[PDB]
Image 1 (cartoon, rainbow, N blue to C red):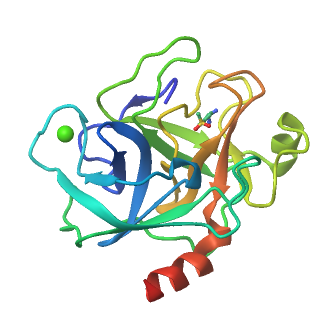
Image 2 (spheres, rainbow, N blue to C red):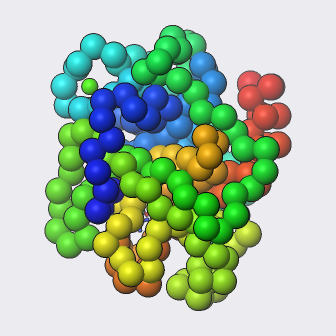
Image 3 (cartoon, protein in one colour):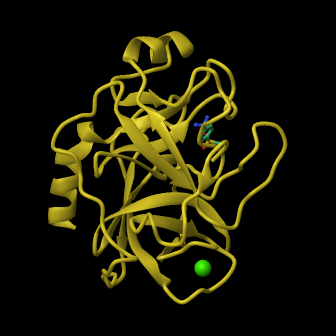
Length: 223
Ligand SMILES: CS(=O)(=O)c1ccc(C(=N)N)cc1
Ligand SMILES: [Ca+2]
């Protein structure tokens, strides 16, 4: 997260870190046994880490649970990043509390102008590299589809939306991938892609979760 602020320990209870010997992507807990992330974050041997703040220091509120199965969206396209979403089932149910909680799925899509909360342990610089150890937060509005399409000609599908600032300076970044975009207490997006980070006229592009509620629900009900 570039241009954000320190969230505060466990203030984003649904945020999870995907670990494969090191943090490589974020994710969101949607129930005691399932996590939603980005399809481009796929890999084998994933351990889900919940209740984390400083990913390099065990503070006492963490829960480390291995993944039992990963399900990438059937129509995921790695070249265009269309349908960049995947589900991860935990080997065992997480213990839910005030510091580890699930985030509700949306019943309707969020409209442009709505303010959302984006979070992650990704790079904090637009130029250079600096990874924080604690969770960073960023409040950003959803942009109109017209401004999004104008920023990325011929690259935005109906399953994507832009959020951020056209002026640049504030945006999600490498390492925040798979992370949540929460608006009005509902999960509306997944950190997916963008050109660089916090660049002028290049806002972040996010997976539009509201288009996948049916797939998510039916998949969880049969696996
Ligand atoms: C490295 S990545 O493709 O995951 C990526 C993730 C986020 C952004 C940001 N501009 N919103 C840019 C790139
Ligand atoms: Ca920790």
